[PDB]
Length: 178
Ligand SMILES: [Zn+2]
Ligand SMILES: [Zn+2]
Ligand SMILES: [Zn+2]
Image (cartoon, rainbow, N blue to C red; front, side, top):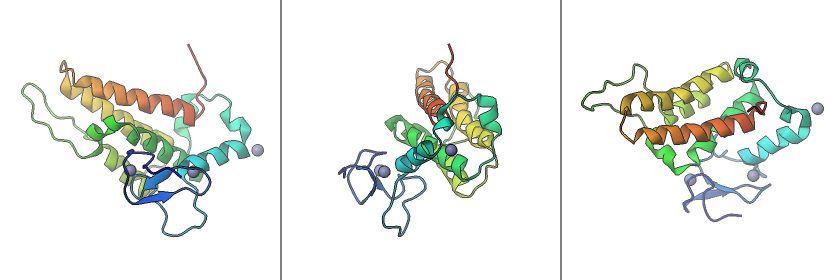
């Protein structure tokens, strides 16, 4: 196994996957690492199994169809993995916890959003379709862009949204376009 957390790349109290060499802190893994279960497989392994059980799941999809899907177990897992993939980038730190807004010449967004709130929302099964989760994710970056305006800090939101969007297209097998 690895000696660092796959998500935050630090050492500490880790839990090791039984079917791959990754390891995780308890609350870096999503869902949080399960109390018992021996063996234990991590989210990367679970996602791989879904693909291997239904190879045609990797043929192209239209985003519109994906968004309308109900959050049944397999879609729930895929959104948890996509959330995880964002927390894997160190720039997610800017978007994790509840933000506040007091900048000369800007007003705060009408609907604040942050990653830990989405995490909690997924945990408490508050989204009924993929669209719900995707909307909150994109809201995070959109709020950031609107608030920071011409400050170069806006770029952080562009960069982390690019991470989200590449992973979204991969995990949900969105049809490749030019
Ligand atoms: Zn970690
Ligand atoms: Zn694994
Ligand atoms: Zn099949």
